[PDB]
Image 1 (cartoon, rainbow, N blue to C red):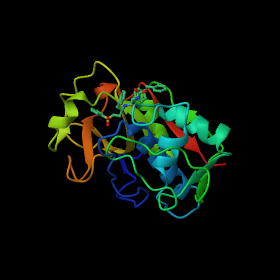
Image 2 (cartoon, rainbow, N blue to C red):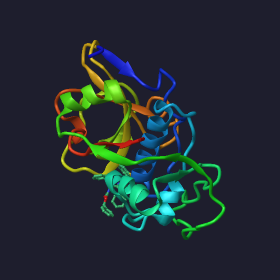
Image 3 (spheres, rainbow, N blue to C red):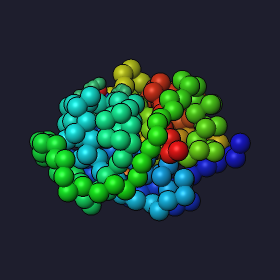
Image 4 (cartoon, rainbow, N blue to C red):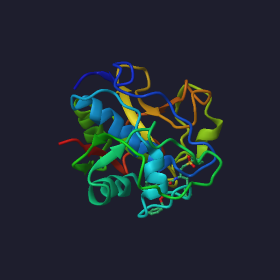
Length: 215
Ligand SMILES: *[C@H](CS(=O)(=O)c1ccccc1)[C@H](Cc1ccccc1)NC(=O)[C@H](Cc1ccccc1)NC(=O)OCc1ccccc1
């Protein structure tokens, strides 16, 4: 494998977004994965709709949590594989209240056929990401409010609570690390990203990694 991969620095990741005061992390995670995979499948890099998931994905709980695997399944099984653009279905849940689902006025920007869940194995997760692009992952982000920059080694790792986007890794550094896109604006962390140590299941990053599949 390449000693270091960074799909953001290659230009395959959209800008860091703002989930606001809403428990929508799962939506931003999943949509960010679909954005990258869509571009990597031979389509333009598009901003896609978290709000579609927040308002209409009734297998999840909108501003009160969800699973990226649930959201991928809902897209295929309930929304005919379609993902709307961010512009046609814009985020409106930044204050904690999601508007009702609307079934008109929205425009497709990407389609997916399914999803792959990845082995609970950091090494195999790295090997997958190096070839197939960024990965949606769940983490223990309880220590992350106090994150300021640098390779976080003190990820208190007791419970999954957050959904984020694994965009790369760097094995050549003194302490190898993952590179994670967050959804808390660029004023948090390293212009919206965070680095956690790689190889000791920091933040329980191995436990629920997955990715959409563009047929
Ligand atoms: C988003 C995380 S966050 O709000 O940005 C955040 C992160 C770190 C610290 C502080 C805040 C939400 C937060 C939330 C909101 C309501 C209830 C619980 C959690 N996190 C989730 O949605 C979690 C993330 C997760 C965890 C494990 C595996 C995948 C993703 N998801 C979750 O709690 O799912 C519960 C669920 C709801 C409905 C259907 C199935 C499962």
